[PDB]
């Protein structure tokens, strides 16, 4: 998957 503004860092991308 694409990247989304979330998590501890924010702009993170997923493998899906």
Image (cartoon, rainbow, N blue to C red):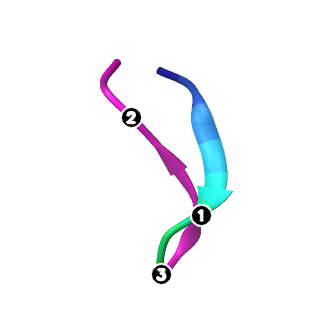
The secondary element bearing badge 3 is classed as loop
Vertical side of 1 occupied by 12: above or below: below
Q: Mark 2 or mark 3, which has the lower sequence index?
A: 3
Q: Give me the C-alpha separation between circle 2 and circle 3.
A: 14 Å
3 vs 7, left or right, is right
10 vs 16, left or right, is right
Q: Position of residue 4 (x, y in %)?
A: 64, 46
Q: Magenta region: which residues?
A: 9-16
Disc 3: which residue:
8
Residue that appears at 39% across and 34% down: 14
The secondary element bearing badge 2 is classed as loop
- In which quadrant of the rendered view does residue 16 lie? top left
Disc 1: which residue:
6
Residue 7 forms part of the magenta stretch: no
Q: Within 10 Å of the Cα at label 1, are there few (<14), some (14-19), or many (20+) other Cα atoms? A: few
Q: Give me the C-alpha separation between circle 1 and circle 3.
A: 7 Å
Residue that appears at 57% across and 26% down: 2
Disc 2: which residue:
14
């Amino acid at each position: 998957g694409p990247c989304f503004p979330m998590g501890p860092w924010g702009p993170f991308c997923i493998p899906d």
